[PDB]
Amino acid sequence: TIPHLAIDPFSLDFFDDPYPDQQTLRDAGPVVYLDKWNVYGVARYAEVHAVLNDPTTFCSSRGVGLSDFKKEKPWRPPSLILEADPPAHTRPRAVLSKVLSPATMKTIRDGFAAAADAKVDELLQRGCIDAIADLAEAYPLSVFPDAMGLKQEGREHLLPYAGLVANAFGPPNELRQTAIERSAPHQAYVNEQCQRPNLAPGGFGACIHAFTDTGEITPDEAPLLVRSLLSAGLDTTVNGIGAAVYCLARFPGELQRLRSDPTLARNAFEEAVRFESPVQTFFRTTTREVELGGAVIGEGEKVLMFLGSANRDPRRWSDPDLYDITRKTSGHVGFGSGVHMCVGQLVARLEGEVMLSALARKVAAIDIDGPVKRRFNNTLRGLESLPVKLTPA
Ligand code: HEM
Ligand SMILES: CC(C)(C)c1ccc(C(=O)O)cc1
Ligand SMILES: [Cl-]
Image 1 (cartoon, protein in one colour):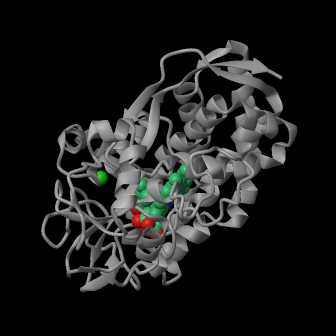
Image 2 (image 1 turned 90 degrees about the vertical axis):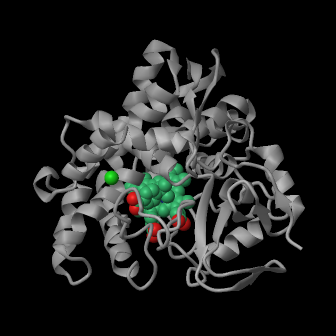
């Protein structure tokens, strides 16, 4: 009844161009079986949204990667938030929510905005820059580690550790094996910065440790909640801002619209998150036998959700393959959906908005003037290099 497919969603050819295979996955049926990894797959918006919003059936505590924590050891201690289910997930969630609160965004918005304007000004003095290393990487590296309260030394470990985490979600292919192989120094740095003495006052990390007396989390839970922000707080933002520049570079009509109205900067970033989906895929594990789209899925089965495919499903989106900065983007699953929907999305959207705002006000043109290089990762979509020439406004 369920179609079986040999498509490997974690192969280099798939990363290089996932969109044809994703239509094949969507049109084959609401639920597919991927013989390559012995998992169920859902690529349409409706089923992906349903799975995300049924955490009791499709749990996260047995792992959101291919590996079933009931069968294998996790490569690192489980995240108290990403790899946890209600009720154990609830209170660590509320703490990270209050740490990354609207009140916290108001305190850091000016500094994030000025750093974005200063970076775009610095890049316009060079002209021909690499939009990944000199922009998508440089700007979040200039605001987020300081906002965490991180020390200067060892920041070179932050992006490698994040790429390691995203790769460890994948199957045991060479990407995952090699990442875990080179992991030990990145782990040691990250875990050490999670301790309370190493987090400067006022920052996100010190605020997490300060939330350990309210009855929501204990002091021994604080280091791993800090680890969550050090795992997730940089890499997806880099790929997201890199996606927006990429989109604005390929669609000059939208850049001209964004210049004419800079208030579109926030939705311009949101549409880039839908269009490129920095987080392509995630797993769930069935806790019971369940019926999903006419398919009966037994207990203990891994279910792979194609978030990026769900954000391009024509059953849900009009002209899904077009970058439209005025699109009604509400409902896209680039940040997830339901109880696990990104708790740090206010930080990502703030960085993305103030960056596109700076580009909208200071840049006249963004032209690709060099070979574009893709970054391959088991979970994330993003570029390794984006050579652009920036024309000042
Ligand atoms: C463009 C930027 C980002 C994207 C596309 C993104 C994507 C996602 C997605 C899809 C999820 C859902 C995972 C799931 O359902 O299993 C998630 C959760 C999460 N994100 Fe983000 N994220 C971004 C930025 C951030 C930032 C800036 C932070 C922290 C400062 C962060 C921290 C987290 C955490 C802790 C979770 C787990 C929440 C939970 O399990 O309840 N993310 N993210
Ligand atoms: C941004 C993604 C979804 C990849 C993420 C979220 C949370 C964690 C964690 O460590 O809790 C790690 C990664
Ligand atoms: Cl680790």
